[PDB]
Image: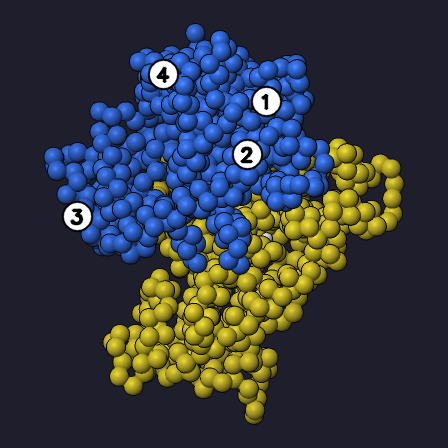
Chain colours: A blue, B yellow
Amino acid sequence: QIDFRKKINWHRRYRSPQGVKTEHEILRIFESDRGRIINSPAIRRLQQKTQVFPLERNAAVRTRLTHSMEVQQVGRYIAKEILSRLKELKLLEAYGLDELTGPFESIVEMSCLMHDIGNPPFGHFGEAAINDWFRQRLHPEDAESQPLTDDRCSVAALRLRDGEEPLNELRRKIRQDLCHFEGNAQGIRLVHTLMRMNLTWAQVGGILKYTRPAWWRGETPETHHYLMKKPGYYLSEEAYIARLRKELNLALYSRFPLTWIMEAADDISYCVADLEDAVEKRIFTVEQLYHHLHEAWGQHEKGSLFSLVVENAWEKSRSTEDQFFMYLRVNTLNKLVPYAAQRFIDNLPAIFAGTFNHALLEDAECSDLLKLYKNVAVKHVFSHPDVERLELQGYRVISGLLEIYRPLLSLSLSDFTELVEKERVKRFPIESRLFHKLSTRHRLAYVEAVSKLPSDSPEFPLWEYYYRCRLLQDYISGMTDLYAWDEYRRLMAVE
Amino acid sequence: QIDFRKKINWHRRYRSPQGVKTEHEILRIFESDRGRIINSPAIRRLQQKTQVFPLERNAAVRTRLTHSMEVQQVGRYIAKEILSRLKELKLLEAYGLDELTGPFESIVEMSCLMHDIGNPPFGHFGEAAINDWFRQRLHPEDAESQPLTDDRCSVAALLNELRRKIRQDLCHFEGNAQGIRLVHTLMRMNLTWAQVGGILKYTRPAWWRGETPETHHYLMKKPGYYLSEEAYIARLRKELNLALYSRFPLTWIMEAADDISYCVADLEDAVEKRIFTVEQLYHHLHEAWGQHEKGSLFSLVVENAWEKSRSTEDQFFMYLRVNTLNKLVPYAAQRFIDNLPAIFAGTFNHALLEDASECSDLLKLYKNVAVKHVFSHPDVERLELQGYRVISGLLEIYRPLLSLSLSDFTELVEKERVKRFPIESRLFHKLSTRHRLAYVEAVSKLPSDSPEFPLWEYYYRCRLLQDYISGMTDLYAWDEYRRLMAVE
Ligand SMILES: [Mn+2]
Ligand SMILES: [Mn+2]
């Protein structure tokens, strides 16, 4: 049975409010969350994180922030559409929404905003350089089966010991979790353990995009593959994630019903904006682009969504660029938003369950239009040398930075712990200074996770390392494209 | 009589919608406006326009954009508060709001967002360098009375009343006035009248020469619009039911949010730039209050937030922000409702937080601390001075286009390639196509025959230049300065 009272959890993890609360009181909690998000430095960082194009000396181009604001307004429209349609169906009171109208909407907007929140400096390329650097040092493939006589792992504790141990399973999970860094998973890690925001369960639900644990190694459940497409959370969050499922009434590997709305907007905004920027960076004319889109459609009919959207917007522009993109955007939303709004309502039971193994804008006419934009963007924009140059640049910056911090990892627990207590250590001065370079928040978080472990435990050293790596990963992922590059040069000694 | 149906004008200037429209249809028009604003490049430019502190290699510091988002959430709260209070008073249906709930709120947020949108690269300092550069070339003081035997104006053409108005308008550039110019004539957004009302902060015309309006002193504190907009501005007044020099009732809400967000954010950034500790700051605030009582708003806000803190800094600012809004927002929400007739009239000669209000005092306290410690910092001041030269120098680089005859200038507008003026050609190409387009359009609307026609051309010519510059980000203007000075 569909009841949103049960999904829109206004309680918190720590210092949580409890007992009754009016429609207004509840609105205020959700409005509190907005203020928390909007004033966050993690949200400010996004104006300095690159979105497709390099951070040029004129802000004409979209950054991760300006894009996420655009995504949020799309999300607002979809949510608002779902609501209006449902009030016309009178199912609003029936689904326990008549009083959670505003909250619903705000959650969407705020999750929209926070997509890309945990992404590393150089995005998907950052992810690569991180995962790759860890892979050459851990080799999680060497953990999959029985203890290999020749384990490629550089860490003594994480190397599968031959002797009959269930500790071998702990090593397996750590190796896969650290080598499978994902922005969404880092986003969850960020809002809770790092940024220490203390948001409503419902909000944190909306930013939980995937249900796959980072430590996952096998084949994906056939009836869960879509939902477990990448990883959604780390081993460090597993505890809190369980807490989240129970609070939001979610089964293992079940998604929060609103996440689907936020996802949709992101999928829409996704290309069109970069395509606008492409003509702005003079890659081709607006006319040239129209012809690339005509070429891309192929199977042309005079009543298709191409004619209704792209052909339509092209005619509006002639008796230019502004008008073109302005109406192209309009045209798209005006057809796509209703579709996804409907799709949501249509498949609401499975969505409420968070079991629905599909996207609002599927694969089989809306999905086609999007794909068309994507193809054009791939073949002409994403392929541009200045883009690719920066993509490759990013990779080295992160890889090199990770190597600069290798000495802290290439250490014994006894030594590392020593550095954590005494800030000034005799024999390890480089390591000292390098550890000071780390941000006070990720540093704090490490210690806290460590102090919660049992000293006596044989798993304790493995955990320390898992956390040690997490700590390093947090520092790096936390950086902006600029800061990471600047630091790379500074630590390579060229400034 | 108070009816918001009459103030929340969902019609547009060009391609305007008309006839009935449902609550939903109306919401959609206001939601359309949001999309227009949010996708605007003029709104993107703000992530590259400096807010107090220089850009820095880490975005830990607020930019004009990140501040305006903060302002918008404050505005949201105030608007939402006014509404909730009014629903409790049941006056919502009574004031024609029961169906314009969402719109009201969106307008606030969108106007909040668009405050500073018309600000130049080096904001306040940019204004100076512009106005100063024009003043040495026009001397509008020399126009005030009778034609001076020794007129300091560099322009032959600068009917005596038209000359007066042009000189004052061009020499009195203001971000808010430029903002109005921007959304309509430059950005060609075509927004709902109501939205454009919300960004009209001042009722003073830029061409005004005759110190202080007595009865309308506060509303005409700074200029609100240019001579180039006077026509459209008249159109706006009539559409929004405003008397000459009357303000849009919602503008007051947006304004308030800005007055609040104004300092606290830079104070957070001050501790972030290590200017002083969070502890050092608390002591500067204790020093600043002086007249200490154990139940005052200082104790309730600052003392309160200080105790909560004992990350420390995060918690401190987080709850300090909370504490402030939790007391100030209700006040301004009330003030609005309390003085609603005069606000609806847009005649109310005061601010929501203004009088001897404990609220106004708290704000002033933040401001004083910011002035005495943050705004006074050398790296700030250095950049402020730097900005001035960049703009002044840039204005001088473009002096050749102004130091020209109409006959010559016009020639350059038709033929892109002109023989004798090659520097001027290339310099004119440097200007953005939008401001270029806008100039021509304003010019083509004038009567060729008219004796005022040459004066207008110049007014517009200067406006065109001003648009280019004001349109730039701190970075682009600096980059260009160096590029045109030949150091890259
Ligand atoms: Mn996105
Ligand atoms: Mn401001």
The vertical placement of A53 against B408, above or below, is above
The vertical placement of A244 against A408, above or below, is above
Give the percent coordinates (x, y) of residue B130.
Answer: 53, 71
Q: Write down the residue under mark 3.
A: A291
State which chain disc 3 sits on.
A
Q: Write down the residue under mark 1.
A: A461
Q: Are marks 2 and 4 on the same chain?
A: yes
State which chain disc 1 sits on.
A
Q: Is residue B233 at all visible to an observer of this figure?
A: no
Name the front one of labels 1 and 3: 1
* Circles 2, 4 touching at the beta carbon (< 8 Å): no
Q: Are marks 4 and 1 on the same chain?
A: yes
Comes first in the chain, label 4 or label 1: 4
Give how far apart the Cα atoms at labels 1 and 3 are: 61 Å
The 10 Å Cα crowd at callout 1, few under 14, some 14 to 19, many 20 or more, is some
Comes first in the chain, label 2 or label 1: 2
Residue drawn at the location 55% of the way across and 39% of the way down: A407
Q: Secondary structure at mark 2?
A: helix
Q: Secondary structure at mark 1?
A: helix
Comes first in the chain, label 3 or label 4: 4
Name the front one of labels 3 and 4: 4
Q: Which mark is residue B121?
A: none
Comes first in the chain, label 1 or label 3: 3
Q: Secondary structure at mark 4?
A: loop
Q: Write down the residue under mark 2.
A: A409
Q: Write down the residue under mark 4.
A: A218
- In the image, B230 versus A110, the foreground residue is A110
Give the percent coordinates (x, y) of residue B69.
Answer: 54, 44
